[PDB]
Image (tube, coloured by chain):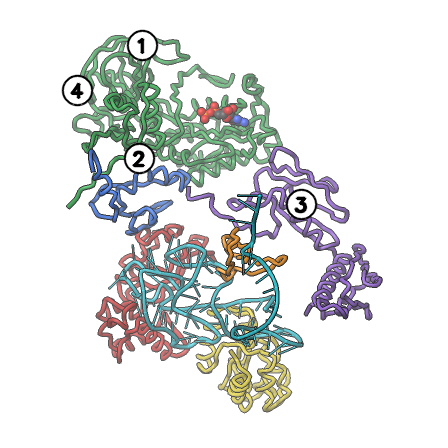
Chain colours: A yellow, B red, C orange, D green, E blue, F purple, G cyan
Amino acid sequence: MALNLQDKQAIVAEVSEVAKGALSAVVADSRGVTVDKMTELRKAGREAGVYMRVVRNTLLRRAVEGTPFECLKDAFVGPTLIAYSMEHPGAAARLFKEFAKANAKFEVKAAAFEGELIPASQIDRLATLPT
Amino acid sequence: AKKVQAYVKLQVAAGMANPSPPVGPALGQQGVNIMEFCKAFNAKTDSIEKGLPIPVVITVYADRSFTFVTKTPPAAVLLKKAAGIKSGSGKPNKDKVGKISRAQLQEIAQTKAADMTGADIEAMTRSIEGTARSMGLVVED
Amino acid sequence: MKVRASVKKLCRNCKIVKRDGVIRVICSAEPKHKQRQG
Amino acid sequence: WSGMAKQYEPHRINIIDTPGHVDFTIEVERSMRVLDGAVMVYCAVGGVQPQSETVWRQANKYKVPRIAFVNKMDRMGANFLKVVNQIKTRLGANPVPLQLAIGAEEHFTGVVDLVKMKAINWNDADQGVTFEYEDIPADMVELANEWHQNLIESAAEASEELMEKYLGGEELTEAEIKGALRQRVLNNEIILVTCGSAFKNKGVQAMLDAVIDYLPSPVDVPAINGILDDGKDTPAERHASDDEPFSALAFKIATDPFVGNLTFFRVYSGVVNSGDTVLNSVKAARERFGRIVQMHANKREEIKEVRAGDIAAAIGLKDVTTGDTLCDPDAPIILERMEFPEPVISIAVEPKTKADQEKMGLALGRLAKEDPSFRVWTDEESNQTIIAGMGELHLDIIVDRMKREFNVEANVGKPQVAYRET
Amino acid sequence: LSRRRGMLKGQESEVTGVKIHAEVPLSEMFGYATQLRSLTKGRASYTMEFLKYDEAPSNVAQAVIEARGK
Amino acid sequence: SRVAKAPVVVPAGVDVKINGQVITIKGKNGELTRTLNDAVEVKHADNTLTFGPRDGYADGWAQAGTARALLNSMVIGVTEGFTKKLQLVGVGYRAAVKGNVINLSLGFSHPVDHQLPAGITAECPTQTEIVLKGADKQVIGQVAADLRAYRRPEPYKGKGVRYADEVVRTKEAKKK
RNA sequence: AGCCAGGAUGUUGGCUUAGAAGCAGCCAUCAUUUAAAGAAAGCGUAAUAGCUCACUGGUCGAGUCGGCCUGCGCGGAAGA
Ligand SMILES: Nc1nc2c(ncn2[C@@H]2O[C@H](COP(=O)(O)OP(=O)(O)O)[C@@H](O)[C@H]2O)c(=O)[nH]1
């Protein structure tokens, strides 16, 4: 029930935290159960927070209206079904890879967890930080 | 994983959980045997109460294996003998769901949050809160 | 079928058609809902 | 009987045919008890049916050892194994197919024995006297041998060491096979299934040697226990051997104009001889015994002697009725059988001519003695009698029995229900 | 049965079918078995036993009052 | 109509012949010719086939769409061909085929023998099921329904000729 | 519109402590979960089932959705 005004409103509200934040994740779920989208959302909330709604938002202009706030080269998510989840504990955290680890186990698809060109990261694990 | 052969969301009084010819003409067509029907379901129920229907799963195996993780009866369902009132939904707006208190309802929602888990236990608190007020009357605390 | 002088949709599956200028009712669900005219 | 040219000693098999409708089901109740073994007939295409299962329960009540025949292999859609499975899963049985089918409806010619591994291929209905055995028709023996393996699988569990011997890689002989299977088949373990079409006359000729070979003899089957006013555990063991005082069991009463009464009975123990004395130990009555007519290719065989296990029919005496014991004055008075089905459908009845209700009452008296599974009532509302029967047909073939037997026409009706007021 | 008069009071699982209790009026069971055989393909039975008495609006009893007169 | 607004992009190997209105379309299977509603303007236009409602014809758009659908199926027929699949439910209901005639033992009194139309190749992977292949969709569907109508599926145990995908809605004989 | 999933964990909502079990005994119930779960309007209803309430989700991308008044028509509409 996303009206054009309400659409741009919900898109912007869910996009600002990703625009000014860190690297997060999204999924590609056109075929999943209520249980799968309920338990995955509970899991994502225990990992990071209960703020992520498992609803999908891969419409033809949701990210093309919300995402273009910053790092606009990261707008390649106009693809099919997407119901995302954040990762406040560090960019490209464990949560930022557990989804792709679980992509073939108890889940349909996870949009590969593309990450984001906040620092223009390339194909690698964004954890080049010694401890 | 076996298919739909013993599908009944029903748990009879769990002095013996779900007796065979006690349930009704839906559970009669279920091949699950009785040797371990109440072996681990008549004793291991002590985690909530013994004598009340254990909300459980109906998952058995085609290999005659029977595995399920029983969830618990709701605090409101226990709120027939545990929360005072034997009545509940249907007239919680025309009746009371009982002298239900949240000092006990919250404690029960936190300590019985094993079966129904979630991201936050506050979620299960609100879960039970909706479960109780689904009658129209819930512990008012 | 019924050729009631008042054909109506009785079902989510009933459909109005006008084969050859005649107003019939076709319930995919109920073949009792099969009506001819009016 | 003796066998299919393969024969061994004529045996007097005593045979009572059975009807197929549960309506007159006492005929199965008594005649399951009276029975030593049991031939579970079957439609090789029909399989098991609401009466196959009904009579199966009937049989279960008497725990009778039953092997099964699968007739009608010539009719299209008949398959022995399928019906086998039908029995196994509709009745929960262990259908050892000691035979096999050679053909189905168009190519049914013989039966594959799984032990002879041969197929006697008779001729048809009348000529099925050709007993030209045929060895291992490979077409069938591709798996006839593995169906023999099923049979062997049932015989191995027959004994403790027999299973081990089967695990010795060793086979079983033509006597250890049967005797192991039999020794419990006698005790109702597993149903041996052979196929045929008695219309087309195959299978039947073998379906008489497996009878001799497995069906308990009155000497193989456990001994029956009588009953007294007080029913003991073994109030009177009435073993087969007619060493006991004459002690038969009368199960049916018949009619003949030139012979009069034609009561039927299976003698459990003892021997009565062409004029003797016995009491209605169950009725506490008494009388002589005049003109036994044991039935074999019936020529009014007015036999002067009937003995252990020998089913015959007596004439005269006075009263014996369907489960009532036949006992010498020594009187193991009762045989456990005091049961017959209760009418599940009652109905009022009245004559066509109004002054025939007394004759229809008496007709119901006779026709109530003629089968125990048919009660008569006489309610007090007006006068109407309630012919409580087993089935619609059970008491509807007696409403017409008055028309046939008692030349009276009747119009049935619902019983008037007692409507009390307060 | 609901069609007949039978008031459902329980039913379970019995063995292969289910045993079904219902205190059906006696009037409503006068060919039941026959109907049952037809319904179940001859594969079911019923056992009925007068228990009590009750009422159902049927002036049918008022009808049978007109006997040997009105 | 909305369909009319979509070109019939011809495949590779199909020969189109836009003769006036009537048009033939060749493919790997064969050649199909169709008489367009006079309200249709259709062109090839470089491996395509576009339809436009003729002027003077208010009912041109839908008729052009009918042409778009009629020519799309024709293409697919001449390249691929259309294949209908039927079943025989019922005992002893068998439908062997002998070249172009199906010897049906559907148990009336008589052998039903259906001679196939020219262009229809019937196959029976089983005693009791048919696979019509043909170039034209309407006619093969017509043939399927023709066949099915001889011993139609029935509402109790499904017995009768049914389409392989046919969903026979049955019911119980009676309570009695 | 079409096409690709989904319509919970109390969830048989206690819900007339037989369930009318997500859709007859009866009332209110997202309460993480959500686009979903309505906790009922045909399928079982006793559930299930797969469609049902819906809803999102995706697809692709042009209008589309409904009603009001309206004009003219249509049917209704069979005799010797
Ligand atoms: N084709 C075939 N017909 C049979 C067979 N047995 C009986 N029939 C026929 O079916 C009818 C009834 O057979 P029968 O056993 O005498 O009747 P019953 O009193 O019902 O058991 C008769 O017309 C037989 O010819 C069989 O095994 N094969």
| Viewer-side label of 3, 1 | 1
Q: Are marks 4 and 1 on the same chain?
A: yes
Query: Which quadrant holds the C terminus of chain F?
Result: top left
Q: Which amino acid does the dot numbered 3 rest on?
A: Pro
What amino acid is found at the position of numbered circle 2 in the picture?
Ile
Where residue B73 appears, x then y in whole percent?
Answer: 31, 67
> Which residue type does callout 4 highlight?
Ala
Give the labeled residue for mark 4: D284
Between disc 1 and disc 2, the foreground one is: 2
Residue C20, given in percent of the width and then of the height, sits at: 63, 57
Tag in front: 4 or 1: 1
Is D409 above or below relative to E61?
above
- Tell whether label 3 touches label 4 (CB within 8 Å): no
SS type, badge 2: loop
Mark 2 neighbour class, 10 Å CA radius: few under 14, some 14 to 19, many 20 or more = many
Question: Which residue position holds label 2?
Answer: D345
